[PDB]
Structures are given as structure tokens and as C-alpha cells.
Amino acid sequence: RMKQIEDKIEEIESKQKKIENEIARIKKLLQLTVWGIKQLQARIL
Amino acid sequence: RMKQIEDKIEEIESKQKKIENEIARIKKLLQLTVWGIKQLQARIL
Amino acid sequence: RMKQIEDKIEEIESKQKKIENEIARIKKLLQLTVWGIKQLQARIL
């Protein structure tokens, strides 16, 4: 039962790292879209 | 003590699924905004 | 071995709060980009 607890926490930790990596990707793409909107407003203005 | 720990893990897992669903929602909306920017650019060019 | 478990649970919980704060920041900026695209579309159409 103690091994199951340890393994569960391992699985949670690996998954949290994947979530963190995905958040990092999301922030970068979000910043691209900010920049993209900025360029389009400046072209139309 | 082991039940206390297992209960804590259960709350972590619940929260993690909440986070995962939040990130799915974000990625879907980000996909839309990327698309919308691509459409506007094509229009103005 | 037992206190490593306790340390890790508490570190995962902390990391989940960090992640939820990042998600809240992402959602705010997303809502801004949604608004900006809507404004640009209206201007060009």
C-alpha cells in the first residue's frame, strides 16, 4: 500500500511536469498572437 | 496516516483534472484566436 | 521514506496553486486578444 502511494505520487509529478511544459507552450503561442494583433492594427492604421 | 495521505492524493487528482480541463479550454480558445488572426491578415493583404 | 512522501505532497499542492495562478493570468490576456481581434474585424469589415 505504501508502494502504491509512492508510485501514485511519481505519476502525479511526471504529469505536473507535462502540464508545466504545456503551459510554457501556451504562453509562447499567446504572446505570438499578441504580437500578431499588434502588427495588424498598425497596418490598418 | 496512510488514509490521510490517500485522501490528500485524491484531492490532488481532482484538482489536476480541473487543471487539465482548464488547459483544454484554453488551447481551444487559443486555436480560435490564431485562426482569426490568420483570417484577418489574409483579408488585409 | 515516509517524510519524503509528506514533502512531495506539499510540493505538488504548492505547484498546483502556482499553475492555477498562471492559468488565471493566461485567461485574462486571452480575453484581451479576443477583444482585439473583434475590434480589428469590425474595423476592416
Image (cartoon, coloured by chain):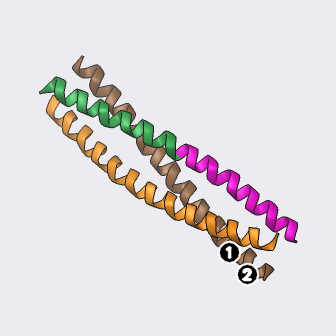
Chain colours: A green, B brown, C orange
Label number found at residue B8:
1
Q: Is residue C45 visible?
A: no
**SS for dot 1:** helix
- Residue C9 part of the magenta segment: no
Residue A19 position, x and y percent, is 59, 50
Local crowd at mark 2 within 10 Å, few (<14), some, or many (≥20)?
few
- Residue A18 part of the magenta segment: yes
Please state if A21 lies on the left or on the right of C31 as rendered. right
Q: Amino acid at mark 1?
A: Lys
Identify residue for label 2: B4
At 67% from the left and 52% from the top, the residue drawn is A15
Q: Quadrant of residue B32?
A: top left
At 74% from the left and 62% from the top, the residue drawn is A9
Judging depth in this view, the residue of C43 and A41 nearest the camera is A41
Judging depth in this view, the residue of C24 and C8 nearest the camera is C8
Q: Amino acid at mark 2?
A: Gln
Q: Which stretch did the figure color magenta? A: A1-22
At 60% from the left and 60% from the top, the residue drawn is B17
| Residue reaching furthest to the top | B45
Residue B39 position, x and y percent, is 32, 26
At 38% from the left and 54% from the top, the residue drawn is C25
Chain for mark 2? B
Residue B3 position, x and y percent, is 77, 81
Q: Is residue A7 above or below residue B27?
A: below
Q: Quadrant of the N terminus of chain B?
A: bottom right
CA separation, marks 2 and 1? 6 Å
Q: Are marks 2 and 1 in contact (CB under 8 Å)?
A: yes
Secondary structure predominantly adopted by residues drawn in magenta: helix
Chain for mark 1? B
Q: Quadrant of the C terminus of chain B?
A: top left
Q: Are marks 2 and 1 on the same chain?
A: yes
